Image: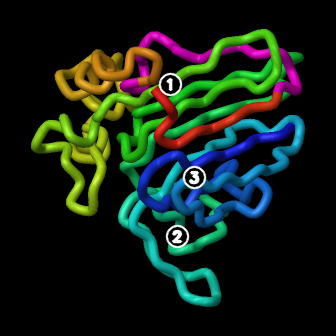
C-alpha cells in the first residue's frame, strides 16, 4: 500500500511510521513546511500508526530527542511515540478490508487528515485547535495536549478495569474532534475501506 505523508504546517515536523515492534518503511523523516514523504506499507500490516513529532533535534547518527512523539530517541522510529501524539491508525488486509481511524487517546499534537487516495470510503480529520484550547492539567510542558490517561494514570481515564466512561477531559477532545477516538471505549469512529486501499496523512490539512 502507498501512504503519502504531507506536512502542510508552517513548522517542521518529523514524521514517524511504525507498527510498534518495527519501522514502516524508513520509520521517520524530517518534513519541512510543505514537504511530503511517500512510503510503502506492506500488505497485512496490523496495528500500524503514523504521527508527527515536533521540536526535534538529531545528530548525524539519527539519535536525539523530540518534544512530542519521541520514539526512543531515534529519527527512524521503530516503536510508538511518547504522548502527546495525534495518531493515524490503520490495519490493512484484515479479512478483506482495511480499517482506519484517528485517535486522541494518546493526546493531540498536530492537526491531521487521514483519507483514502483510492475509492470507496470516507476520510477522517481532527484539525481543531486542540492545543490552544487544551485545558490546564492536560497542557504538556513540551507542547501539545496530553490525554488524561497519560496525566492521571488510573482506569477512570485509562479504561484498564471495569467499564470506563467519558470524562470532561475525553469530552473536550470529542467535542473538538467528533471523528477521532477520545477514550478507549468511545463509540468507534473507525472507517472500513476496501482492502488494499492507498492513503494520505496530511498534517495541518487545508480547511
Return the disc, 1 or 2, that comes first in the chain's sequence.
Answer: 2
Residue that badge 3 annotates: 34
Tally of numbered tags: 3
Color encoding of the figure: rainbow
Residue that badge 1 annotates: 125
Q: Secondary structure at mark 1?
A: strand
Give the residue drawn at x 68%, y 41%. 48
Q: Is residue 183 magenta?
A: yes
Residue 59: which quarter of the image?
A: bottom right
What x and y, as percent, mark residue 123?
62, 19
Q: Work out whether 67 lies above or below 10.
A: below
Mark 1 is surrounded, within 10 Å at the Cα level, by few (under 14), some (14 to 19) or many (20 or more) other residues, namely many
Tell which tag, 3 or 1, sits nearer the viewer. 3
Mark 2 vs mark 3, CA separation in Å: 26 Å
Return the disc, 2 or 3, that comes first in the chain's sequence.
Answer: 3
Return the disc, 3 or 1, that comes first in the chain's sequence.
Answer: 3
Q: Secondary structure at mark 2?
A: loop
Quarter in which the N terminus is drawn? top right
Residue that badge 2 annotates: 72
Mark 3 vs mark 1, CA separation in Å: 18 Å
Q: Main secondary structure of the magenta part?
A: loop
Quarter in which the C terminus is drawn? top left
Q: Work out whether 33 lies above or below 164.
A: below
Residue 37: which quarter of the image?
A: bottom right
Q: Work out whether 175 lies above or below 26.
A: above
Identify the magenta region.
182-197
Q: Work out whether 101 lies above or below 145.
A: above
- Position of 53 compared to 61: left or right? left
Give the residue drawn at x 89%, y 37%. 43
Residue 146: which quarter of the image?
A: top left
Amino acid at each position: 500500500a502507498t501512504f503519502e505523508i504531507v506536512n502542510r504546517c508552517s513548522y517542521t515536523v518529523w514524521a514517524a511510521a511504525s507498527k510498534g515492534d518495527a519501522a514502516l518503511d524508513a520509520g521517520g523523516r524530517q518534513l519541512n513546511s510543505g514537504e511530503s514523504w511517500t512510503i510503502n506499507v506492506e500488505p497485512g500490516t496490523n496495528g500500524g500508526k503514523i504521527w508527527a513529532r515536533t521540536d526535534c533535534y538529531f545528530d548525524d547518527s539519527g539519535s536525539g530527542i523530540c518534544k512530542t512523539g519521541d520514539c526512543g530517541g531515534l529519527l527512524r522510529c521503530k516503536r510508538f511515540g511518547r504522548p502527546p501524539t495525534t495518531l493515524a491508525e490503520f490495519s490493512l488486509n484484515q479479512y478483506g478490508k482495511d480499517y482506519i481511524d484517528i485517535s486522541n487517546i494518546k493526546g493531540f499534537n498536530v492537526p491531521m487528515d487521514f483519507s483514502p487516495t483510492t475509492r470507496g470510503c470516507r476520510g477522517v480529520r481532527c484539525a481543531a485547535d486542540i492545543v490552544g484550547q487544551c485545558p490546564a492539567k492536560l497542557k504538556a510542558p513540551g507542547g501539545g495536549c496530553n490525554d488524561a490517561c497519560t496525566v492521571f494514570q488510573t482506569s477512570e481515564y485509562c479504561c484498564t478495569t471495569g467499564k470506563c466512561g467519558p470524562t470532561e477531559y475525553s469530552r473536550f477532545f470529542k467535542r473538538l474532534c467528533p471523528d477521532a477516538f477520545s477514550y478507549v471505549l468511545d463509540k468507534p469512529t473507525t472507517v472500513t475501506c476496501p482492502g488494499s486501499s492507498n492513503y494520505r496523512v496530511t498534517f495541518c490539512p487545508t480547511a
